[PDB]
Image (spheres, rainbow, N blue to C red):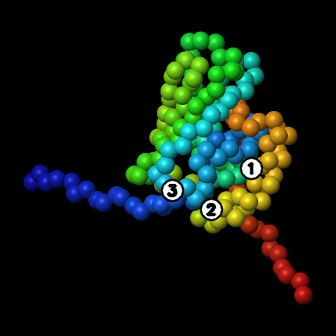
Amino acid sequence: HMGDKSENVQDLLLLDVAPLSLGLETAGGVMTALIKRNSTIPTKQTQIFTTYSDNQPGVLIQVYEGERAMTKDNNLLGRFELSGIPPAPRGVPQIEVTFDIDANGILNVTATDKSTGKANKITITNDKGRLSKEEIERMVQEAEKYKAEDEVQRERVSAKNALESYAFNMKSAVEDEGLKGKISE
């Protein structure tokens, strides 16, 4: 009368290398790759980032999926704020951000406040990505053209690795291609 619930198999195959670059967007909407593309995963990389504040020192980690110097035109992957810092952040102590990928398919990011010795994490699961497979191709192919823009806008915005306190990602809804074109002879 009382049986057991048959569990289904829920594993899946992932990629061996990172098809895209994972990292943080710097104040300005420019993608700052922490884990670059073509890297063997799972992998754990750590890079040093800084923070820019308006009036109150607040650190927010904007995690983005893909290599895109136009991150402000795209949708953010994840974001976690760092708070609970006893000492006064003067902008001098840098923020250490570590991206540790697990074989199960989860991205465990961990930011360490070198100002107080605190560490915060969040398990982000994208599996195969949030963007469409067709868009993944653009994220790879166009990554080289935005690479040229990157070095330019990087200095123009004056943000190499500066994380902003609050990133306002506008929910720009992608429009369905209704532009009926035609080739000419």
Q: Compare marks 1 and 3 and give the one earlier in the sequence.
A: 3
Please tell me whether residue 71 is drawn above or below residue 157 in the rendered image: below
Helix, strand or loop at label 2? It is helix
Q: Which image quadrant is residue 3 in?
A: bottom left
User: Alpha-carbon distance for marks 1 and 2?
Assistant: 15 Å
**Residue with the mark numbered 3:** 40
Q: Amino acid at mark 3?
A: Thr
Helix, strand or loop at label 3? It is loop
Image point (22%, 57%), residue name? 6
Image point (82%, 75%), residue name? 181
Left/right placement of residue 158 relative to residue 138 reads right
Label 2 crowd bin: few (<14), some (14–19), many (20+), radius 10 Å: some
Image point (51%, 51%), residue name? 126
Residue 61 on image: x %, y %: 61, 34
Please tell me whether residue 19 is drawn above or below residue 180 in the rendered image: above
Choose mark 1 or mark 3, whichever is in front.
3
- Residue lying farthest to the left in this orientation: 1
Left/right placement of residue 82 relative to residue 152 reads left
User: Alpha-carbon distance for marks 1 and 3?
Assistant: 23 Å
Q: Which mark is residue 11?
A: none
**Residue with the mark numbered 1:** 69
Q: Amino acid at mark 2?
A: Ile
**Residue with the mark numbered 2:** 136
Q: Is residue 109 visible?
A: yes
Q: Compare marks 1 and 2 and give the one earlier in the sequence.
A: 1
Please tell me whether residue 27 is drawn above or below residue 180 in the rendered image: above
Residue 120 on image: x %, y %: 50, 29
